[PDB]
Image (cartoon, coloured by chain):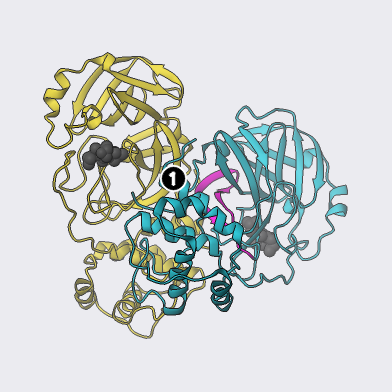
Chain colours: A cyan, B yellow
């Protein structure tokens, strides 16, 4: 029993993390097969971060400029190119620890595990979610750039995030493994602000189901509601509009508890209109929205890898 | 920036997790060098969980009764003994992946990382704390027994917890790696209840310091206080008594923020007497007490391994 924020076992990704140095700057890189993946802003100098022309800054760079340190050993660089906002450094040695991997662009509301690193060495691991505004609330200090997010299913690692920057608001923005930024963010030190951070409604319901399973049933009520009428309360509280697909995704949880999705939507509406009144649900005094329906099933059924 | 609940990289421990089968029961075991460590209640049958005599149940067990599966391979068992509440199965093959390890009995209030497993295979990782009542609030399903807790410093893994059971109250109890239970708990299906779960005061202050660093300063006030007078508010709210050693441990955080420990104790007292009034600190609506002073420094300075 018990429900916790759980990251995946990070072993398979540790062995893909390297140190990448270009000139005076060091950041983390991911090393699968004979390619090292890192953010392209490794090549920006002290005064270039405001408005760099990355194509031009590349002309003045050759293979031997990028120094890649694996653990304590050196990797020989034999090719490089710029794909969107990441660099792809072809090294001469395939990584012996390359797990079965895939590059996936995840959707807002989905969650992943982040292995925070500095100088190509791991520091820790935490579970994050792609906010509706395409930012993540994580823990990154200077030099964590290149840290990656991923999901582990069976024996296959699906890489979905590479960290690029912190915004003036203290939140984080990054790209997928093809170099495309999540959201309208660019790798420049310009004025860019995240939009309204709405709540992942389908994820709050999944967490309420997880609570029922774990013995917390005080928030269950004698009301029900309809989708259209529930969405009208969600909009007032900046909650993501709940669709029928979301309802279908909650089926397995709805069947395991004998609680209709709409009856659970009615209890949520009460929480939004009346607050928690100093009560706690799964040890928390606010509504948690960083658990997907699959996240709950995974932890409440004990899926392994 | 950003402050998160962070587990250590779990790679070095994954390669020590095995499956242990004894008769009809399967649970997880830890495999360092040529010894496999598992809970001794692997040998209890369906009707034995109420009042087992583990010495007697051992007489009827020999080496070939314990089947140890490493990944998908079989380990040959050549010796076994019972130390407190864990078994020590001597196998004939040293583990090639044995990290630099140590067995440590941690103190109430300290934190560690837990790698949850089922059938000797990892499922995930989360950060826990040893409550003052010697229980932990974690996520364990049937078969997670044998999952271990640990800290990683430099390249050395300090194992401190092996999970044994869930209590009728939904919390968790276990042992150190010498088999001694944390708290007054036994590996029996008897009536055992955890005591008062008081709050780790030194850990709440460390988390308040982490908040100041990350931009949340609304809880800082114009008051101060004394230790004796603050403890009198702590006792009313079932908070662990704050000693001078605790104050000394908070020095480094106190110096990095230019905030005396006692001035921070005064802000906490206000939170306890007046509540948070619907405000959030580091994204949470209650006072978090599962971050040690070293946990905060680690994450706010970027320590790696
Ligand atoms: C990659 C992470 O480690 C965070 N980070 C970062 O996003 N930028 C992008 C731009 C906003 O400054 C950056 O330039 N640096 C270097 C130091 C802070 O100026 C930096 O550390
Ligand atoms: C080891 C973990 O997986 C949890 N767990 C457990 O603590 N006990 C000890 C005693 C209270 O029942 C136990 O017997 N089992 C087997 C199934 C539940 O009866 C069990 O799964």
Instruction: Residue B157 in the image: state x and y as whole percent.
Output: 39, 38
Q: How would you classify the magenta stretch by its main secondary structure?
A: strand
Q: Which residues are magenta?
A: A110-132
Does residue A80 appear left or right of residue B41 in this picture? Answer: right
Percent position of residue A254, x then y: 46, 55
A31 sits left or right of B300 in the view: right
| Residue at image point 35% right, 21% down | B68
Which is more toward the observer, A286 or A57? A286
Q: Is residue B302 magenta?
A: no
Residue count near mark 1 (Cα–Cα under 10 Å), binned few <14, some 14–19, many ≥20: many
- In the image, residue B56 sits, relative to residue B135, either above or below, namely above
Residue at the location (85% across, 58% down)? Answer: A53
Q: Nearer the viewer, residue A29 or A67?
A: A29
A7 or B254, which is in the foreground?
Answer: A7
- Asked if residue B253 is positioned above or below residue B232 in the image, the reply reads above
Q: Point out residue A147 in the picture as x, y percentages from the top left corner.
A: 61, 49
Q: Which residue is mark 1?
A: B125
């Amino acid at each position: 029993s018990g429900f916790r924020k759980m990251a995946f076992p990070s072993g398979k990704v540790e062995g893909c993390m390297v140190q990448v140095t270009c000139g005076t700057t060091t950041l983390n890189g991911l090393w699968l097969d004979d390619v090292v993946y890192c953010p392209r802003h490794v090549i920006c100098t002290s005064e270039d971060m405001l408005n760099p022309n990355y194509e031009d800054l590349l002309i003045r760079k050759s293979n031997h400029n990028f120094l890649v340190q694996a653990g304590n050993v050196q990797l020989r660089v034999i090719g490089h190119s710029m794909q969107n906002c990441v660099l792809k450094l072809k090294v001469d040695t395939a990584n012996p620890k390359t797990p079965k991997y895939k590059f996936v662009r995840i959707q807002p509301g989905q969650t992943f595990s982040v292995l925070a690193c500095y100088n190509g060495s791991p520091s820790g691991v935490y579970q994050c979610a792609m906010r509706p505004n395409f930012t993540i609330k994580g823990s990154f200090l200077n030099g964590s750039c290149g840290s990656v997010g991923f999901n582990i299913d069976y024996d296959c690692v699906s890489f979905c995030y590479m960290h690029h920057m912190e915004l003036p608001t203290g939140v984080h923005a990054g790209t997928d493994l093809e170099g495309n930024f999540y959201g309208p963010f660019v790798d420049r030190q310009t004025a860019q602000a995240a939009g309204t951070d709405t709540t992942i409604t389908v994820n709050v319901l999944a967490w309420l189901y997880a609570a029922v399973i774990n013995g917390d049933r005080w928030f269950l009520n004698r009301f029900t509601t309809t989708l259209n009428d529930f969405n009208l309360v969600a909009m007032k509280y900046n909650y993501e509009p709940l669709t029928q697909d979301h309802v279908d995704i909650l089926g397995p949880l709805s069947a395991q508890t004998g609680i209709a999705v709409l009856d659970m939507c009615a209890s949520l509406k009460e929480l939004l209109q009346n607050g928690m009144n100093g009560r706690t649900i799964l040890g928390s005094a606010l509504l948690e929205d960083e658990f997907t329906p699959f996240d709950v099933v995974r932890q409440c059924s004990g899926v392994t890898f």
